[PDB]
Image (cartoon, rainbow, N blue to C red):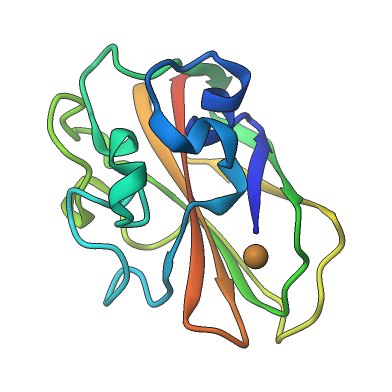
Length: 170
Ligand SMILES: [Cu+2]
């Protein structure tokens, strides 16, 4: 269990009350857990941000103004997870929406570039309670986008899904 605390994920911003009417996830942003195997398997289209758990379906809403967006620059960024339970880990992956994705429609695999812009494969090692990855957000993205951070667990069928709402500039 864990969440991306910086830049604050959509679920974490629900706990901080930067996002409103998120439902149960406000009280458990670390628990956005579904099956691993994304994108070949994993949470169904339209239900990625919720990890396809019905109680988190508020996170599957998508309008241009629904979610509070962090104003980030492209290029070097840092993504920091807070882990409330440090599970044997397969990988951490970071995906970003395609340049011409539609912020008014549900998030699907077609919304995202399915090649993650960076990936860290831990080989089952136990991570620390705070994990930070440094990657370059692609420069060809501008304006409103969603970054999907995915944590694949090595010794279960599960993964944690952390959508992050961003507004990108040079
Ligand atoms: Cu856990």
